[PDB]
Image: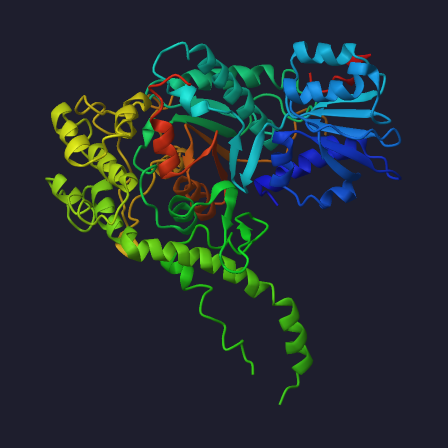
Amino acid sequence: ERGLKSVVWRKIKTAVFDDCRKEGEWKIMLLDEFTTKLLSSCCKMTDLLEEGITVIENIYKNREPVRQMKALYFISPTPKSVDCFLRDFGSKSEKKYKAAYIYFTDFCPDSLFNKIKASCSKSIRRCKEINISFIPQESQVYTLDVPDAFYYCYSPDPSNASRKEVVMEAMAEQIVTVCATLDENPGVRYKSKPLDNASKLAQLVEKKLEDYYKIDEKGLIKGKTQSQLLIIDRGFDPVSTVLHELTFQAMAYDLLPIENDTYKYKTDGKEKEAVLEEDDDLWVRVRHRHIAVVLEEIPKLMKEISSTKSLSALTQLMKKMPHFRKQISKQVVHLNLAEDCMNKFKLNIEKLCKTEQDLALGTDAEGQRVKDSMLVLLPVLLNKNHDNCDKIRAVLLYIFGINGTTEENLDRLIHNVKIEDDSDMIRNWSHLGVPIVPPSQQAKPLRKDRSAEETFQLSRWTPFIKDIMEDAIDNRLDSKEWPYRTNYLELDRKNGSRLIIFVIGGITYSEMRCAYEVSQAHKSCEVIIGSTHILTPRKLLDDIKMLNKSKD
Amino acid sequence: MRDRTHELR
């Protein structure tokens, strides 16, 4: 329970399925891109059967009429998603199914609604808006559906300012649904750190949910509840985005090519694929553990075959092996993928981490103070044996470590260190509110001390949100840097204390741990971070350039 | 609004 996926499912099931569920009969469900991702997120597509769904189809693709079954339209308020519906009841007026049951993932504009109401049913026995416009990526991490948000959020200043406002409200209203699903009416507090986007957004959200609840028909929540929403801009921590993190999940999506949470084989023959989801429950116990601790907590070997191979429990060991043929089949996948990472590690990543941690901390490796840090960066130049990706990442740390660098010295690097093309992977970081040419700036923030224990002496770096999460739970947080019988009562449960965090421009898998580790160390409240997307070092760099060019 | 069914008719 509580797992973000569950909460969403618990809502969809009672808001949608139960709402149009007739015990004796089943119906056809239609989904667009988003809703498909939404459902795939929090349920096996078989669980639907118990909910009154016998057939699911793509509302986009033309379909065969079934004028005997009722139709459940679970879609977003998208022009495309709605046009397709109107192509089932509106145009040609040639009805496709007995009746229609429309459930919009979010509020539906009058423009589209008008086109719906007018034409032409009748058949439309229901048009309901449930307000779920986010993806329960993990049981504590969410991600919105705001295409090309990052770009338009940190674009130079061309005609890409009208579309930036578009992305802003999209994020705002999309974030609001996150609250509404948790049944929380938080207090919006931004950061006064880089740029000022988080403040503008914090205003859109604060206003957005002031209108929401003022109209919410669920009637559960009205007036602020015991939870606070933090909106922070990406500039606040450029470091953690670039670090070659060592915790399993953050290192896999970084090193290996794991597009769409699906890591591809071998092994073996032929090459299949595996999915890194929470239904695995094995990868859930490992995705946040350090690479070494990972291996030494499930690997070699429970062998030779446990206590096999006088046999009183002979049949027991015969049946116990039949079902255990899957526990090993899964332990293998989460081991091969672990190998593919272990390799890239011993090959050069290991050496790359040595001088990265000492630079990101600038005083790590016991070397207090350090002084000349450009001496620390050197190693990663002849150890290449490297990719221009790792090279830029290392330099980025150096600059972040010495804040605003010089204009001339920076130039020499982009020359006598190759990195000719893809040079903007360093330049454009200034658009995110991080000094690139002007020395100093805000002279850096102030983070927590200890620095207690830190095995491996490589991942001694802690993302700045963890010091923010605790700075929120422990209450101690700068108010200037983080603005804003009878009786009656207004009961009551359940939700309780929740810390909702939302970083703009994406979150790292290393920052995701922070949510778990902090909420796991605590219990009096659950931290919940999110964004428009999840970040990987490379994908970030790619996105971080291209900024100075209006697409095209 | 959250339930527009009535609004259709």
